[PDB]
Image (cartoon, rainbow over the protein chains, first blue to last red):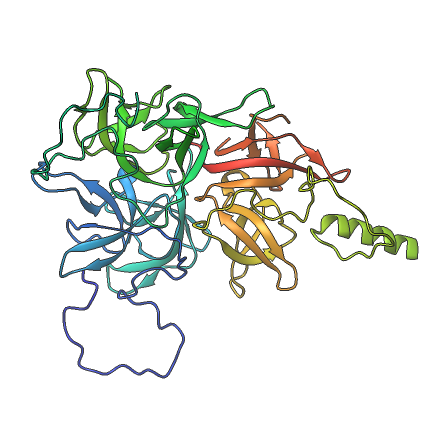
Length: 154
Length: 152
Length: 168
């Protein structure tokens, strides 16, 4: 629900090990990032963090915004949110992405697609392949490493 | 049918207003431009300016060129033209473009497709969404702000 | 035995991109035309500085072929192997044999260059097969810009431009 946890921790972190220290919700961006990636920023409608986003049009008084969604309305993938300005960082669907995305509440090689709420689910229109299994961060919060490369063909 | 108007105006322009000054036909490129965008150039066959283009092949003596077109042959979007060299600047369909494009003689949010002449029309195989109403520059020339983000 | 050895060397060197081979003479190629029709040619005829290029461990010999992702027992990371159809992931534009690393351009980025063809005139529609070879026609926008050039009794290359997916 938030990039940074709302409640402050009561304990320090044990910074000794180096394994399995990347399965956190505050892991913004992608696991493998190219210097030739196209990155945009939009006004955020809701909390579309780590979800497929779509274009949301108001009454014309205010500019275009982005909200979590999928299906035929999918426009990109949100990889970061600046909360002070409400700015959602979006990687366009034309550009391929590899990273941790929210999964609907799954094995490597299974084909995934974005549902109505911008959540990955097992399969049609979007090329997404899971590179790992679901990792549970909360009772309803599951993340999964996936590679999204364009849109499929009907 | 030229980016730069041929008939030079008889009056000086008044630079007093900062609103509604970009709704001209000589506004080449895009409104939102990324420094990592891929930009190609090709020989132009006709005037494909501000239209969707397709690859056209000749007899074989000369190289391939780009001509205004759509359908399943759509290759990219022509954003600029150098008239001296007849060189059309193309953004491939694999790259996403946001800018003013020619509309066939539509409200923000309407899905659009490219016709046989590279003109956007209201609706199948291209992701084009109108971001503004049709602005009429000439009695037959209409433009529209559209974001293209690939195929469907 | 040695003749069979030499025959296998010939086969594997024809398979390879730039095999090591000593020559008794200095071959002279003074003309500057049709000098680029070699198997050791660079990945792209027209290359942009904004192209996204990845590298992956290779399974088999996917050079100048369409590549797809493949997974094993999970002990080792995913690897690219020659393939096409609906499983196509990218195009292998280079290979480094010492490190066994295939340099690949994803299907989300348009590519133009010489690719392996099935054993064709310009302006024809091409599709990737199960082996990653191009064949005359589909779900990929691949168009041939030239005719098939034959370098070996089974090796054909063709100049092709591939730009994204083809809806419907």
